[PDB]
């Protein structure tokens, strides 16, 4: 996930990401978008809900 | 709205070959997801294949994987299906399937919004 997205998420309320077959590594990049109220992770191939 | 026309099936032998096809008319740009759906006689329809419109990622059902090959002709707005060494399990009713944007249904007829006439494929 781009770091700039993580930075701007400080005011984001809804985020949707589509990887269409690409495995997505969060590597703990979600604890700065604290304003988010809706999280959509479609075709991101996690195989595990991130912490 | 969007209409689909397909052909290229019929009666073949196990060990024959077929070249399925389907052409699209109407709104050709708005269609995001394309695939094939086959229907056994009296049984539920099965999503045969799936393809991203411009992302270009191809998908197929396990029962037809390695035997059925999707083909798309952007020039003529056509979707083909080329298969060989068929099996009697391929005898089914195949419908041209198109889905607009927002949906990520590879082989599920749940959200596809346009279907073709239906071509009977017979493999003995």
Image (cartoon, rainbow, N blue to C red):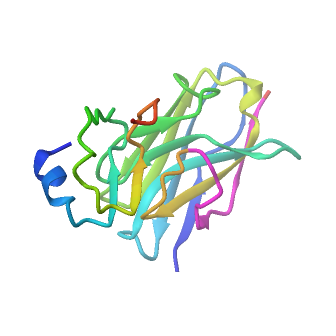
> Is B18 rendered above or below residue B116?
above
> Is B103 rendered above or below residue B61?
below
Left or right: residue B62 versus residue A29 is right
Residue at image location 33% in from the left, 61% down from the top = A36
Does B121 lie within the magenta span? yes
- Kindly give the residue lying farthest to the right in the view shown: B42
Residue at image location 45% in from the left, 55% down from the top = B33
> Is B55 rendered above or below residue B60?
below
In the image, the segment drawn in magenta is: B107-123
- Kindly give the residue lying farthest to the left in the view shown: A4
Q: Nearer the viewer, residue B80 or A1?
A: A1
Quadrant of the drawing holding the C terminus of chain B = top right
Residue at image location 59% in from the left, 56% down from the top = B96
Percent across and percent down for residue B37 are 64, 48
Q: Nearer the viewer, residue B40 or B81?
A: B40
User: Which quarter of the figure has residue B62?
Assistant: top right
> Is B99 rendered above or below residue B3?
above
Left or right: residue B31 versus residue B11 is left
Percent across and percent down for residue A43 are 42, 43
Does B1 lie within the magenta span? no
Percent across and percent down for residue B3 are 55, 72
User: Which quarter of the figure has residue A19?
Assistant: top left
Percent across and percent down for residue B60 are 52, 35
Q: Nearer the viewer, residue B75 or A19?
A: A19
Residue at image location 67% in from the left, 63% down from the top = B117
């Amino acid at each position: 996930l781009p770091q700039v997205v993580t930075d701007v998420g400080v005011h984001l309320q809804k985020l949707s990401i589509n990887n269409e077959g690409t495995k997505l590594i969060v590597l703990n990049s979600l604890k700065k978008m604290v304003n988010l109220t809706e999280l959509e992770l479609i075709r991101c191939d996690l195989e595990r809900i991130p912490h | 709205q969007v209409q689909l026309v397909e052909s290229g099936g019929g009666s073949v032998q196990a060990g024959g070959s077929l070249r399925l096809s389907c052409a699209a008319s109407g709104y050709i740009y708005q269609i995001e997801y394309l695939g094939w759906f086959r229907q056994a006689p009296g049984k539920e329809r099965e999503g045969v294949a799936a393809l991203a419109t411009w992302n270009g990622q191809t998908y197929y059902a396990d029962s037809v994987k390695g035997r059925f090959t999707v083909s798309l002709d952007n020039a003529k707005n056509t979707v083909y299906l080329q298969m060989n060494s068929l099996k009697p399990e391929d005898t089914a009713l195949y419908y041209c399937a198109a889905a607009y944007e927002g949906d990520t249904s590879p082989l599920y007829y749940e959200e596809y919004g346009y279907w073709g006439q239906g071509t009977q494929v017979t493999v003995s």
